[PDB]
Image (tube, rainbow, N blue to C red):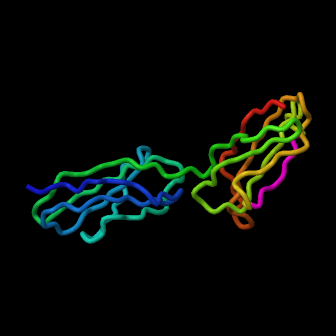
């Protein structure tokens, strides 16, 4: 009797928030009920409702970097349409694609994609063969998504690792660090 909304598409995805989009059926409806929750969510899914004129809903207060289950229900008062469920993953707090685009005997070029949250700066550590602990680190004023690494001993195994710091002062927290191995 009633067509269920579809054309489901996700975008405007944020770490703790992300937008969901769906098309509106061609039959008279009173609005859609939005229910969303993660697979590991509590047996009590969240309840979000949106007006019929709204086909996109922005979710917030969500765990960054997680697969969320979102369901859309079309209702026309006493009649209900077939449920619609899709899965969307919230971006990850840690940047990504930490790799080298250029390689020099004593230096290397690092490039990575900025996360989905504002970052004050990123911390990058230098990995020297046995310098497992005596690593050398430098900060990254989020000025560029790529940086250059210099002061590296040639012919020596190296490890490049970096930590991203967004909140600072009241709640200085860092995301899980990402590291890679590099031979010099």
Assign the magenta stretch its main secondary structure: strand
Task: Name the residue located 80 percent from the left edge and 48 percent from the top edge.
Answer: 148
- Residues 26 and 92: in front is 26
Task: Name the residue located 81 percent from the left edge and 45 percent from the top edge.
Answer: 125
- In the image, taking residue 44 as reference, residue 112 lies left or right, namely right
The percent coordinates of residue 37 (x first, y second) are 39, 52
On whether residue 140 falls in the magenta region, the answer is yes
The percent coordinates of residue 111 (x first, y second) are 70, 47
Is residue 35 among what the camera can see?
yes
The residue stretch that appears in magenta: 135-141
Q: Residue 53, relative to residue 73: is it above or below?
A: below
- In the image, taking residue 97 as reference, residue 104 lies left or right, namely right
Image quadrant in which the C terminus is located: top right
The percent coordinates of residue 118 (x first, y second) are 63, 63
On whether residue 121 falls in the magenta region, the answer is no
Task: Name the residue located 81 percent from the left edge and 30 percent from the top edge.
Answer: 183
Is residue 42 among what the camera can see?
no
Q: Residue furthest left?
A: 1
- Residues 14 and 174: in front is 14
The percent coordinates of residue 81 (x first, y second) are 16, 56
Image quadrant in which the N terminus is located: bottom left
- Residues 181 and 60: in front is 181
Task: Name the residue located 11 percent from the left edge and 60 percent from the top edge.
Answer: 79
Total residue callouts: 0
């Amino acid at each position: 009797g009633l067509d269920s909304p579809t054309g489901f598409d996700s975008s405007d995805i944020t770490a703790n928030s992300f937008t969901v989009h769906w098309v509106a059926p061609r039959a008279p409806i009173t609005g859609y009920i939005i229910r969303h929750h993660a697979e590991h969510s509590v047996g009590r899914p969240r309840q979000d409702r949106v007006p019929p004129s709204r086909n996109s809903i922005t979710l917030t207060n969500l765990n960054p970097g997680t697969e969320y289950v979102v369901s859309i229900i079309a209702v026309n008062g006493r009649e209900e349409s077939p449920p619609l469920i899709g899965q969307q993953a919230t971006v990850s707090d840690i940047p990504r694609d930490l790799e080298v685009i250029a390689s020099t005997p004593t230096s290397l070029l690092i490039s990575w994609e900025p996360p989905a949250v504002s970052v004050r700066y990123y911390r990058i550590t230098y990995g020297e063969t046995g310098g497992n602990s005596p690593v050398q680190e430098f900060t990254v004023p989020g000025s560029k998504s790529t940086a250059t690494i210099n002061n590296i001993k040639p012919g020596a195994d190296y490890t490049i690792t970096l930590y991203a710091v967004t909140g600072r002062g009241d709640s200085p927290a860092s995301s899980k660090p990402v590291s890679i191995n590099y031979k010099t």
